[PDB]
Amino acid sequence: PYFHSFLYMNGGLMNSWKRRWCVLKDETFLWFRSKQEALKQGWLHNNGGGSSTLSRRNWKKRWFVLRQSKLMYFENDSEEKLKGTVEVRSAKEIIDNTNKENGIDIIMADRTFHLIAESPEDASQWFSVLSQVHSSTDQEIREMHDEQANPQNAVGTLDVGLIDSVCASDSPDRPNSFVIITANRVLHCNADTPEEMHHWITLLQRSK
């Protein structure tokens, strides 16, 4: 990426500030609820625990993070509440079902974990990384690259080309706060340090 860091953003319709992990790359500014540091991360509908009794209607959407041989998932993309953990290399096999349901199966001991995505490409990516870690030594795993930040996981995105103005918000309570202004949108940001801010000001003024 060009640059990345955490940033505190907005006050939408209730003056609510949230810590967001932000990244600029290929002229797109994007912000997440947490740092994207994993081989793959994303939302997937799944039968919790690998229950064969659960009905597909009751399959909850969770936030999956695959880090080494451990495919874990959370309640939110904030990764605040760990909901479960599957050790991929202990699976019997992984099955590519992207053509029937945009899904992947992880066949475990007595049960199978169904992972359903919303697109064939997303299902293909998951199957690919899962299939690879499953048949890979510790060394060959520690050698694997973290996926690049996915635009589909971002809370919101912004083409720098649409930026009309990037200015420092001279606010008393937020000395490192700055405003990003577009034709149909305005968003406030805050940095931990003044240099982090000035750096963002510099980087974001490059297009339009």
Image: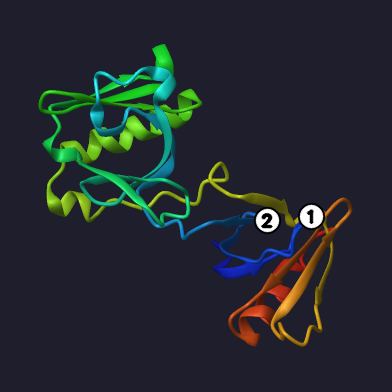
Q: Is residue 197 left or right of residue 140?
A: right
Amino acid type of disc 1?
Gly
User: Of residues 192 and 24, which is closer to you in this image?
Assistant: 192
User: Of residues 110 and 92, which is closer to you in this image?
Assistant: 110
Q: Which residue is mark 2?
A: 27
Question: Contact, CB < 8 Å: mark 1 with mark 2?
Answer: yes
User: Of residues 50 and 153, which is closer to you in this image?
Assistant: 50
Name which residue lies at 73% across and 63% down. Answer: 11
Residue extending furthest right?
Answer: 183
Name which residue lies at 67% across and 50% down. Answer: 157
Q: How many marks?
A: 2
Vertical side of 103 occupied by 2: above or below: below
Q: Is residue 84 left or right of residue 25?
A: left
Image quarter of the C terminus: bottom right
> Could you tell me which secondary element the residue under label 1 belongs to?
helix
Q: Is residue 49 left or right of residue 189?
A: left
First in sequence: mark 1 or mark 2?
2
Tell me where residue 130 sits by quadrant.
top left
> Could you tell me which secondary element the residue under label 2 belongs to?
loop
The picture places residue 79, in percent across and down from the top left corner, at: 41, 54
Residue extending furthest top?
Answer: 100
Give the label on residue 161, or none: 1
The picture places residue 31, in percent across and down from the top left corner, at: 60, 57
Label 1: how many Cα within 10 Å (few below 14, some 14–19, many 20+): some
Tell me where residue 143 sits by quadrant.
bottom left
Name which residue lies at 15% across and 54% down. Answer: 139
Image quarter of the N terminus: bottom right
Vertical side of 110 occupied by 61: above or below: below
Amino acid type of disc 2?
Glu
Vertical side of 161 occupied by 18: above or below: below
Label 2: how many Cα within 10 Å (few below 14, some 14–19, many 20+): some
